[PDB]
């Protein structure tokens, strides 16, 4: 399955920043419109929670833009769009912010790391390394690590997001909103006659 | 049993839900909940106050994601709203007087009488019941009159 | 008299009077609040900003 | 103006 | 009106009348058996001659009172202008949540 | 009804209570400020 | 013949709003944060004014 | 030209409250925010990052 | 099987029962997080010179309950969001409504 | 001595009665009180639920 | 009616030190408290609670 | 002899009037002017040499 | 409204009416031993026929 | 090897110019100029690579 045919894109979540340049000196947000002066941070993993959103690692200079892309929301507030504006190729029908909880680096009394070697929980019953019959004893586990309930195991969440079947759209207007084909600063008068460069 | 994170909480107030704020000078105050029992919900329903769980927050940040307002039409849009003529009402389909008179113990009969009072407008009546243990005392905030964190 | 089925555990009958409780927001100059709250069928909306 | 001994003196550049 | 043998709740439910002029209120608490009953002139049940709180003015019970809660129009309390810090309930006694 | 002169639920059916010179922006470039809810429309019923 | 019986009538005596103050529920011991909980809902210990 | 801004203006204001108060249940903060002398502000887009 | 702690023979036929789960989460749209309807912890939205408390809501109107049934009307409530957790507490039509 | 203990505090009320003003400007001035004598609270007869 | 108020206003106010002090011999109770312009803060009845 | 003291939180109570709002903006005028002031002294409004 | 067993004390306070026509009062005892609750149409309630 | 640095009493300091307000408020308003502003560079006028 090729991304270029059925909107089969998947590595669309693997994006950090796409900062624009308009005349090979100053950035396109130069005119200070965002929190970040120049950089288009799509995602920042845990450095100032205030850049991130409540249940995703995405930086809020792009979080507004994706809501501003096809949907006409972002300034008034945040509507959850009604059941027609979203097709199966538009935003948030493909991605949803998500988190796990694994193990930290240093906390416990005794911690010697375990890889693929000896998965202990119920191996020798169904699958130790390959699909074979019962060949082992009954015994507690090694690798599977809780963080839940009674067991005193402590760690931090590993929060991110997974976008695939969507395309990142940016308008060209003063406000930046895709109201029709022609935008407010898309093909205005300055943005039609003068020549420029792109080193983004 | 240990999750460090942040969350975003918008205005749940019916009267200031979506308003414009005019240029000027203002000051605001809002309260949050430290008591684990009332704020966080459980599936099966159990007290979280004495049972291990505690609430700690590090930083609060206020945000304003407004429209980049037109500055050629700067003084025009504001001055119109700067009148007793231009106002903003926020109505609801359900405009409640949610008081509470339960069925304590083994109850089968429930009478209601309010003495001579003004009645002007009306939309309807709704009737349903939920456990006394399930509900907290909403006077000061938290009380040991609540444990059912479901 | 609201006669009903008996309960096993103590409940709370949510009495709902669907009456009017709407706001009206002004701003005469830059830093003013003339916002009018009203409890109309209550008739107890005695004070507002 | 200062509520001790009032005076008016300003210079514009 | 009295408060039950171990219970600690009571309302006031009196019908509509003209409320033209007022000066204030004064709540007070006193035992039932410590107080005689009027009307006939003589009491049989009142087998307690001394330490009468109401008919003399001597009053040790006011301190036990927990919270004054006022409502006329069934919606808003005494200051319908949200004057005092706690608008509905008016605390006399405290369970201690903020000792400030 | 004079008690709704402030509340404006009785004062003008649904639109003309504020400055009627700002109706331009709603019917022509409304998409930016889709605003018919800030001023919430009055209820009407025959009798 | 077996059932246990009380002449209970709830129709005459009213059921007006029990006003949502800061603790007037029927009988909840519940739980407080770390400072111990209130015993009963309306028992003789709330009279004892306690500080932590 | 008769519409949206051409001069420089930031869309968001990453504001911090001046005084703090923490107690048994409440998490009070008296934030002192003044809306810019020309620009407007929407309330449906206003939130708290905790 | 055995009435002993530590060492016993009869514990060989010990049957283990799994503990029941309970998800500690949040109600729809983080509701019950701020004191909107509460009166002691009321919002004071004032001016820097004006100093007038705008936000007034009593016990009789649950402000969080008010917008929630209006959230039932604004589009479909089945559309999930992360900054606005559209976590409608629900069950399967097979779980409660038993289809024997 | 070296002991670990926490106190408790309780008030008293002997031989005095409760007193409250019937005023908007909270001050019990005269028989013609600020709100108690005022016509809005002295109109047609209304309910009571204290 | 001449000397009265039928408006929404507070009666008792509480503020915290924004700049909390934790030195060996002094605590600077640093309040950024502004008086209400249509209010009258009584310096006669202004006190600290420790 | 084995004792230590530290402050935690300080609550500022300025229990102010529920004064007439129209009068609150007007009855300041003379003291708001250059002529009037609140001069306040003691018997011991003095300095000491030791 | 009934008089319960061992509970001889009876209250009556009817809420404020718009009542006009009156020729007087009337009061008398009635027995649940001999009265059913009529309104449904049919009642097993009457475990008597006195 | 077992050693750590912790923190206990933190302070900010600011040694202002004790000026006459006559010249202080005039030239802060003259630095409030659209043209007369402030600019600071570096001796290390250099970018970096990794």
Image (spheres, coloured by chain):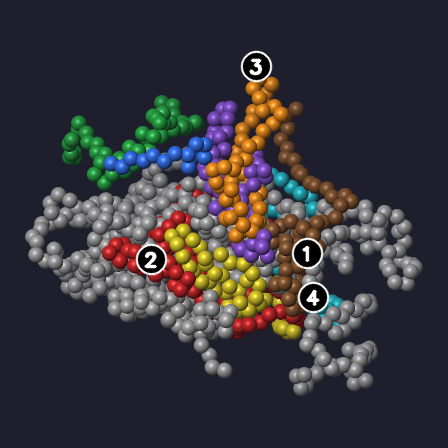
Chain colours: B red, C yellow, D blue, G cyan, J brown, K purple, L orange, N green
Numbered badge on residue L49: 3
Q: Badge 1 sits on which subunit?
A: J
Residue at coordinates 11% horizontally, 47% vertically from top-left? A23
Q: Badge 3 sits on which subunit?
A: L
Which residue is more in the foreground, A100 or K24? K24
Dot 1 corresponds to which residue? J32
Above or below for A83 versus I54 = below
Residue at coordinates 59% horizontally, 57% vertically from top-left? K1
Q: In which quarter of the image is the C terminus of chain E?
A: top right
Tell me the CA gap for discs 1 and 2.
46 Å
Q: Under tag 2, what secondary structure?
A: helix
Q: Badge 2 sits on which subunit?
A: B
Residue K50 point in image, percent of width and height: 57, 34
Residue F12 point in image, percent of width and height: 42, 73
Q: Under tag 3, what secondary structure?
A: loop
Labels 4 and 2 touching (C-beta < 8 A): no
Dot 4 corresponds to which residue? E18
Above or below for K45 versus M46 = above
Tell me the CA gap for discs 1 and 4.
16 Å
In the rendered image, residues at marks 2 and 3 fall on the same chain: no
Q: Which of marks 4 and 3 is in front?
A: 3
Residue L9 point in image, percent of width and height: 52, 36
Which residue is more in the foreground, M31 or M11? M11
In the rendered image, residues at marks 4 and 3 fall on the same chain: no
């Amino acid at each position: 399955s090729i991304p270029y045919l059925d909107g089969t894109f998947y590595l669309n979540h693997t994006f950090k920043k796409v900062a624009i340049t308009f005349d090979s000196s100053v950035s396109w947000p130069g005119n200070d419109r965002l929190l970040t002066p120049n950089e288009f941070e799509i995602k920042r993993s845990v450095d100032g929670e205030g850049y991130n959103v409540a249940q995703c690692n995405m930086t809020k200079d792009w979080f507004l833009v994706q809501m501003l892309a096809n949907y006409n929301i972002g300034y008034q507030g945040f509507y959850i769009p009604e059941s027609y504006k979203d097709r199966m190729y538009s935003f948030f029908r493909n991605f949803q912010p998500m988190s796990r909880q694994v193990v930290d680096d240093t906390k416990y009394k005794d911690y010697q790391q375990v890889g693929i070697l000896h998965q202990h929980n119920n191996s020798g019953f169904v699958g130790y390394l390959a699909p074979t019959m019962r060949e082992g004893q009954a015994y507690p586990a090694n690798f599977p690590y809780p963080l839940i309930g009674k067991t005193a195991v402590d760690s931090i969440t590993q929060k991110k997001f997974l976008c695939d079947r969507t395309l990142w759209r940016i308008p060209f207007s003063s406000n930046f909103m895709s109201m029709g084909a022609l935008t407010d600063l898309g093909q205005n008068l300055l943005y039609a006659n003068s020549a420029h460069a792109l080193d983004m | 049993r240990y999750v460090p994170f942040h969350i975003q909480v918008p205005q749940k107030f019916f009267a200031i839900k979506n308003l414009l704020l005019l240029p000027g000078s203002y000051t605001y105050e809002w309260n949050f909940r430290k008591d684990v029992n009332m704020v966080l919900q459980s599936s099966l329903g159990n007290d979280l106050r004495v049972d291990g769980a505690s609430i700690k927050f590090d930083s609060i940040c206020l945000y304003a994601t407004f429209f980049p307002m037109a500055h050629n039409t700067a003084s025009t849009l504001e001055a119109m709203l700067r009148n007793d003529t231009n106002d903003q009402s926020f109505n609801d389909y359900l405009s409640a007087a949610n008081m509470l008179y339960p069925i304590p113990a083994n109850a089968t009969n429930v009478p209601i009488s309010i003495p001579s009072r003004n009645w002007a407008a009306f939309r309807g009546w709704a009737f349903t019941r939920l456990k006394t243990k399930e509900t907290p005392s909403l006077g000061s905030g938290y009380d040991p009159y609540y444990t059912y964190s479901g | 008299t609201f006669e009903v089925d008996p309960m096993d555990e103590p409940t709370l009958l949510y009495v709902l009077f669907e009456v009017f409780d709407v706001v009206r927001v002004h701003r005469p100059h830059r830093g003013v609040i003339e916002t009018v709250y009203l409890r109309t069928p209550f008739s107890a909306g005695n004070a507002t900003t | 103006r200062p509520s001790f001994t009032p005076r008016q003196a300003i210079l514009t550049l | 009106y009295p408060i039950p043998a171990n219970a600690t709740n009571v309302p006031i439910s009196i019908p509509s009348r003209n409320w033209a002029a007022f000066r204030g209120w004064a709540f007070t608490r006193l035992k039932t058996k410590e107080t005689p009953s009027l009307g006939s002139g003589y009491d049989p049940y009142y087998t307690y001659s001394g330490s009468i709180p109401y008919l003399d003015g001597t009053f040790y019970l006011n301190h036990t009172f927990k919270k004054v809660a006022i409502t006329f129009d069934s919606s808003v309390s005494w200051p319908g202008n949200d004057r005092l810090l706690t608008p509905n309930e008016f605390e006399i006694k405290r369970s201690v949540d903020g000792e400030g | 009804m004079p008690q709704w002169s402030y509340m404006h639920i009785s004062g003008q059916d649904a639109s003309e209570y504020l400055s009627p010179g700002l109706v331009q922006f709603a019917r022509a470039t409304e998409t930016y400020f889709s605003l018919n809810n800030k001023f919430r429309n009055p209820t009407v019923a025959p009798t | 013949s077996t059932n246990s019986f009380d002449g209970s009538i709830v129709s005459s005596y009213l059921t007006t709003r029990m006003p949502p103050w800061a603790g007037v529920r029927q009988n909840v011991m519940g739980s407080s944060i770390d400072g111990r909980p209130v015993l009963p809902a309306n028992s003789t210990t709330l009279t004892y004014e306690t500080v932590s | 030209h008769d519409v949206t801004t051409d001069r420089s203006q930031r869309l968001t204001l990453r504001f911090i409250p001046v005084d703090r108060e923490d107690t048994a249940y409440s998490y009070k903060a008296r934030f002192t925010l003044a809306v810019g002398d020309n620009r407007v502000l929407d309330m449906a887009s206003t939130y708290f990052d905790i | 099987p055995t009435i002993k702690e530590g060492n016993s023979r009869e514990l060989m036929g010990q049957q283990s029962m799994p503990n029941r789960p309970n998800y500690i989460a949040f109600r729809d749209n983080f509701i019950g997080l701020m004191y909107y309807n509460s009166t002691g912890n009321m919002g004071v939205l004032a001016g820097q010179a004006s100093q007038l408390n705008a936000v007034v809501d009593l016990q009789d109107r649950n402000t969080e309950l008010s917008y929630q049934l209006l959230l039932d009307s604004i589009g479909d409530r089945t559309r999930y969001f992360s900054m606005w957790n559209q976590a409608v507490d629900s069950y399967d039509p097979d779980v409660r409504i038993i289809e024997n």
